[PDB]
Image (cartoon, rainbow, N blue to C red):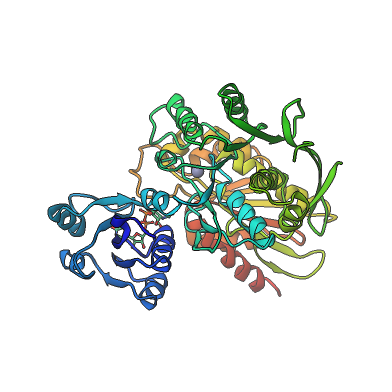
Length: 475
Ligand SMILES: CC(=O)N[C@H]1[C@@H](OP(=O)(O)OP(=O)(O)OC[C@H]2O[C@@H](n3ccc(=O)[nH]c3=O)[C@H](O)[C@@H]2O)O[C@H](CO)[C@@H](O)[C@@H]1O
Ligand SMILES: [Zn+2]
């Protein structure tokens, strides 16, 4: 059953992906949901079809939709408190206002919870874990999504005792949750916008590990430096630590012995601990970082008692999450054909890994160039990590640097996309005209090339565009 406060829930910004998933879980567990949204979308249409009362635009009257007033009001992170009319009315009536993580935590209460968190790779690892659990015939509840924006976001109310969730760390949401199994992909020095320091950002993961239930497990990647530091710290605390990575050791639970990309997909020889011989793990997604994500999902799945062999079988079916090297399309056929992929990489490590995966897919292709179209994400992040972005993009045969993506951030003087292009030693261009990109990439294309659109903003739209301009060139 639902808690008393989650009985009648009014949601400001119910069209959002995470909010839509939360609303559907509530509606499936017997609760009444009303809501409001500034912009009409098809998700609002779906929730209306599921009996939710949604008003387009915000108003105090929305709090009179549910019978007997709303027991709670959930709000999105983009809503502004003392100015949104509905939050003002809700605080004027004494109605509680909460964020999505609090409602998610209340929804995960009685179940065995498996959180996945880290600087990046959360949605991919969470999706791998969900698919592995479902391939074993389980039907867990889940709420994946957040890191890749709205890509990969999906929630579901299952009939089982498990609850998989992606837990964001850039806003202090980790402290809202109580994991039975906590997975930590990596801890990098980024997303420090909310913490003001690096020590605070690492202390948030420390406090998250403190929140694990007694008897629970911390799956963690020890190839990442911060991840290995946290593994050691949590081992001192007498907490079950399941380490996974490439470097071997006397405390490894799952060691990546070898990895090789082939045409079908990749094959990785892995080694598991005796409590959990050398096994083979075949994957359909490209890239060596996908092997580590699969190992994390595998450890998390076996901890709750799923057989590792058929969990590997399930991981072998994973075809990927949107904007995780998602194949946009192709012009031509066989060899001498140009393929267009779309990735969400906005961290220098993400960029390097995506470009390495593209290089590996291109190498055993008997000829081709790696052309990337990078769009830096934030003004502050670009002003900070411009040299990192450029040196990362150096792993491509040609670079196209778009302009900086706003993302509601205040424009900094002297900062633009060219701030990254300064540090690009490979052949590159600067194309701030977003309309002129699709043509210039297609004109610069050549048979057998691997084109990647990379960034966390508008760039995802150029994917199909580059394809069209490529088919126009078919003369
Ligand atoms: C991951 C992502 O990119 N977006 C998520 C971000 O919200 P975030 O605050 O980014 O919300 P966005 O601006 O992206 O918009 C998401 C939804 O918010 C609605 N909206 C927004 C502003 C506003 O003043 N009024 C309003 O109703 C929009 O109509 C939209 O449907 O965290 C929310 C969780 O709390 C998620 O549910 C949102 O999907
Ligand atoms: Zn990020």
